[PDB]
Structures are given as C-alpha cells and as structure tokens.
Length: 49
Length: 50
Image 1 (cartoon, each protein chain N blue to C red):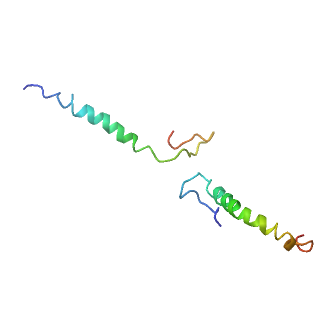
Image 2 (cartoon, rainbow over the protein chains, first blue to last red; image 1 turned 90 degrees about the vertical axis):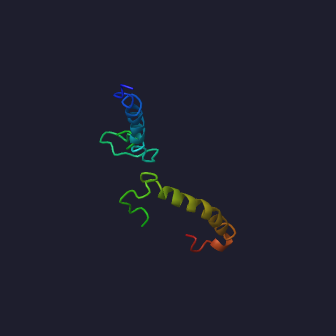
Image 3 (spheres, each protein chain N blue to C red; image 1 turned 180 degrees about the horizontal axis):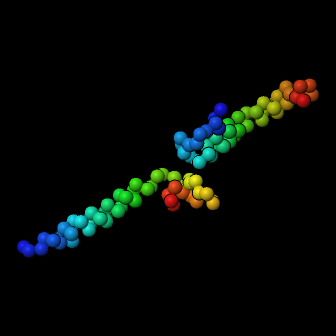
C-alpha cells in the first residue's frame, strides 16, 4: 500500500484546505447588511474590505 | 442623550437606530396627542395654545 503521499494530500489535506477556506470565510461574515468606513464612499461593508 | 453615540454598540444601523426610536414614539403617541389636541381642542383654547 505504497502511496500514502498523497492519499491524505489527496484526500485529507485538500478537503481540509477547502473547509479551512470555508471557515475562513466564516471569519468574515460579521453580521451587517452593511456598514463600513471607506475614504471615498460608503462601500458597504466591512464585508467588502 | 440617546444620540451621544461613540458609535456603535449595536451596530444597527450604523447610526440609524434612534431614528426608529423617535419615529415609533412619534407614531404611538401621535394618535394619543391627536385626540389630546382634538377633544381637547376645546381643552386647547385660544389662550396658551399659542
């Protein structure tokens, strides 16, 4: 049962990259439809930046 | 002393919450002040009604 490199770099580390990205998007949800600071504009929201 | 906001600990809306407050207290107490100025228009006589 040779490789095993990848097999987790195939299965585990790639799906962990996908869901790690997803939770990383859940660290930018911030519950605001909208609000921001925006030197030029409104820019709606902190979501955007 | 509602809108003294280092804003915002709500943050809802980004300085638009008190608009809803004096909005709604405008609304409910409006129809009460209506009759209170209508019934109570006779009890709002041509004296200090001004």
